[PDB]
Image (cartoon, rainbow, N blue to C red):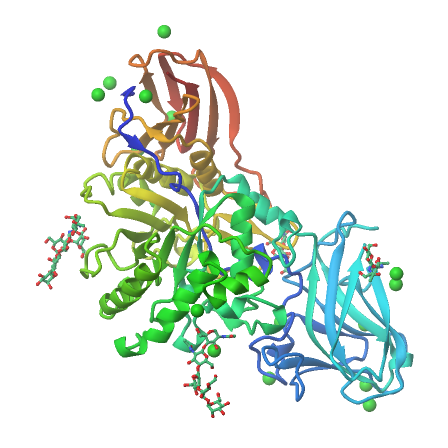
Length: 627
Ligand SMILES: *[C@@H]1O[C@H](CO)[C@@H](O[C@@H]2O[C@H](CO)[C@@H](O[C@@H]3O[C@H](CO[C@H]4O[C@H](CO)[C@@H](O)[C@H](O[C@H]5O[C@H](CO)[C@@H](O)[C@H](O)[C@@H]5O)[C@@H]4O)[C@@H](O)[C@H](O[C@H]4O[C@H](CO)[C@@H](O)[C@H](O)[C@@H]4O)[C@@H]3O)[C@H](O)[C@H]2NC(C)=O)[C@H](O)[C@H]1NC(C)=O
Ligand SMILES: *[C@@H]1O[C@H](CO)[C@@H](O[C@@H]2O[C@H](CO)[C@@H](O[C@@H]3O[C@H](CO)[C@@H](O)[C@H](O[C@H]4O[C@H](CO)[C@@H](O)[C@H](O)[C@@H]4O[C@H]4O[C@H](CO)[C@@H](O)[C@H](O)[C@@H]4O)[C@@H]3O)[C@H](O)[C@H]2NC(C)=O)[C@H](O)[C@H]1NC(C)=O
Ligand SMILES: *[C@@H]1O[C@H](CO)[C@@H](O[C@@H]2O[C@H](CO)[C@@H](O)[C@H](O)[C@H]2NC(C)=O)[C@H](O)[C@H]1NC(C)=O
Ligand SMILES: *[C@@H]1O[C@H](CO)[C@@H](O[C@@H]2O[C@H](CO)[C@@H](O)[C@H](O)[C@H]2NC(C)=O)[C@H](O)[C@H]1NC(C)=O
Ligand SMILES: [Cl-]
Ligand SMILES: [Cl-]
Ligand SMILES: [Cl-]
Ligand SMILES: [Cl-]
Ligand SMILES: [Cl-]
Ligand SMILES: [Cl-]
Ligand SMILES: [Cl-]
Ligand SMILES: [Cl-]
Ligand SMILES: [Cl-]
Ligand SMILES: [Cl-]
Ligand SMILES: [Cl-]
Ligand SMILES: [Cl-]
Ligand SMILES: [Cl-]
Ligand SMILES: [Cl-]
Ligand SMILES: [Cl-]
Ligand SMILES: [Cl-]
Ligand SMILES: [Cl-]
């Protein structure tokens, strides 16, 4: 096919076009991006005197463990303690282990920071060392540190010790431990709370993020981060919704919450940790606020909304407010960040097409109040576009689609027929999740993708060529979900997978990275692809350099050739770069073969006329200079 490129740009490509969608799913927060290594670190939101309260915790030797509702807790936000007792007639190391989130990576080049709180509920004459460390799950110590404690310590006391392993472990089958000498400790009871173990973090931020995951997200070149949900924003009930103010300040004041994916969230990854990550990566937020609906189906009545509207104003003031003018803005300053953060976009709710009966008054009342406080923010509606009719008129809508790979190439012209009437569209969640059109959300046996495939990535890439062509009205787009712990999964496929030790970049990750890193600010019109065909392309140009990015998705089973005609331009470079992602249709990156499918980069001859043979199931980028 001959593709003639117009030397005259039609529109500017928004700076925000490609970004990330985040919620705590598949242990993407706790156990994922948040660097904390201990699971169930503070017994948040568990029922005392149950086995489930002791999740991830195990005795060493004859230790007796129970999670209790502490008559004197370390904080009212953390009402549960671990009650540790050593039987009389004991000797040798006695204590407990934390198995982590299906392991702990022990690396000799890393310094770890361990901490815990303890007290003796009854004053005793105990005198001896409290040792913390890292061991193999077989029981051999890889790193340790200790401090002297006394049984007269009846007040809650924090212990802070560093750990230096000298060996890396051979695998991630390792545990954190806390022990005393069982002879010195025989008959003793100690209450413990609020445990923590951190590795070195991204940009050395206190309470920060896991470095290999954070660097992988930065490598994609994203322009925005949508957070904190997603379903995980909404709660099962009004009482279980995400609340900003429960995620800020001391870890002793963060109660945690049961999220929407079966596990407790510590809220250790809270609002200030998010905002610091954006500052550290150059991403801007698309921040959601809770809008009066929860996933059990309850809408708050219109006359019940006012306190929830004020809580959304407080959340925004924390991000952008003048510290002299509000308590939340003064709180951000008191936490070490008096400058406001960037915030241009706020999403009102999540998937309110499920609650469209009440969204018109929830939208009206939230946006009337929030727009008056923050005239400079763009508020994004979450119902289906224009049905129901909202007031005030939304400037933007969030559109989600999960479909087959074939649907994505067949619908690359989704936005071409939309009116240009001042509304912008956010593709806030998309993915090709299954080859089964009639059971998309089923099992792997019935066509669900365990991991993205070359087929799914090339379909998504065809759909993305249409997002770019229509970027006069499409301002932003994010694959979802972003992250997956391979040992605790509620949804597949996901963009980036990991275990306690390593990260797997999917085919879909490489497609997102190829699109986001090779994006100009000028859209160059070209010959239109066939509407419903397998072969798609989009051309953009960097106004300052004349770098010209030709993106080509062949989502079909046969090779196709393209003849590019750039004879309108004054000058085209004699050479260009080629970046290709291709492989067998059903090939995936997996924990067993994590680099099965990776892009190949080369340099090719180009000029005003050149030909490219797009392999079956491929995503290609050709970069030339034009003026
Ligand atoms: C920008 O341009 C867009 C596109 O033209 C405008 O979008 C239109 O907005 C109006 C409201 O402002 C919508 O009108 C409502 O229409 C429904 C009937 O919907 C059905 O019929 C439509 C043809 O009329 C059709 O477009 C619809 O298709 C959509 O939904 C289906 C699935 O549901 C989907 O398959 C399609 O792809 C579309 O997504 C649908 O089949 C009608 O019931 C409404 O009447 C109620 O509300 C009005 C106004 O308050 C009231 O007077 C009535 O009494 C009643 O209460 C209402 O007319 C129209 O559907 C939108 N069109 C599309 C394509 O979405 C948009 O308004 C423009 N914005 C600006 C800023 O100008
Ligand atoms: C995050 O912030 C949200 C707000 O955006 C917080 O949620 C709000 O929590 C407050 C405090 O719980 C709650 O306000 C109370 O509503 C209660 C239940 O309907 C009222 O009973 C209560 O009035 C009493 O307490 C006030 C002081 O808190 C007194 O000033 C008042 O006179 C009342 O006093 C009686 O009751 C108390 C016992 O509480 C007693 O000491 C007195 O002697 C007297 O008997 C409050 O007004 C809000 O309704 C909640 N708002 C929302 C939107 O949910 C949330 O808790 C924060 N989370 C964290 C972790 O900090
Ligand atoms: C045990 O932990 C202590 C407390 O973290 C470590 O002591 C710190 O070591 C660092 C690096 O030398 C110093 O900057 C801190 O000032 C020390 N703090 C205190 C309070 O002493 C000690 O290095 C650790 N020991 C081992 C063997 O790992
Ligand atoms: C976490 O998941 C990983 C990846 O699936 C598991 O490691 C695999 O385990 C199976 C079953 O033993 C083996 O056949 C594979 O060789 C393992 N793969 C890799 C890449 O190591 C791991 O066992 C899981 N961990 C826990 C604690 O369940
Ligand atoms: Cl032709
Ligand atoms: Cl022209
Ligand atoms: Cl120009
Ligand atoms: Cl039980
Ligand atoms: Cl368990
Ligand atoms: Cl043992
Ligand atoms: Cl015993
Ligand atoms: Cl006993
Ligand atoms: Cl030691
Ligand atoms: Cl020391
Ligand atoms: Cl509460
Ligand atoms: Cl205020
Ligand atoms: Cl398919
Ligand atoms: Cl399943
Ligand atoms: Cl075909
Ligand atoms: Cl072929
Ligand atoms: Cl020439």
